[PDB]
Image (tube, rainbow over all chains, first blue to last red; front, top):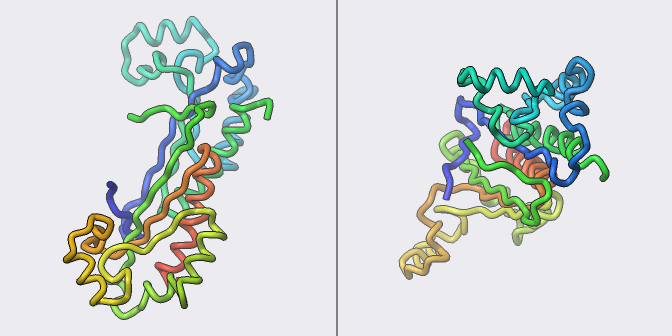
Length: 118
Length: 118
């Protein structure tokens, strides 16, 4: 079962999703480039439009194979994600109505990038 | 952390929420009557409009104090919920994009019933 939502709680609810970037289904498609965009402007606009925090994470997320190597090796925990499957991490917060709405908007926008031929 | 969503999984995702009916904030407001409606037509329309399964559950959900007594006492597990705080149980299923969208729609419609003075 689950906890109950209390509409009168003073706390926001948080929703988080880690959506796998489907590199098996599209082995040569450059998702990282397409999602970040030049200078990361696509993903910036995406976050503004959707009202969600959205991040590309996992092996490949930095597009600089060497910088990733070095950052992983340095053992710093902020870069732990570099070992994970490449994926998009969506995070929203709000009262339930708003939180679901944001997550729905973000998830639908991200699906357009991750299923590029539909 | 969490499991990853795989957009290419053959399985639907399920989202469920149990939203407390706020009887403390509105001690005399008849939420059950308002949500079910005459002959349960409000909640039927609600489910059609939203595309979600929506149910009123918990003590009070049947509006017949006696029938609830008897059904609880009979020990039948389908009626276990009769002991729970009164609440609305929203259930949706679909691929992620659709599932969040449905949950967002349903949660927003249900909030209108549960915060009746906003």
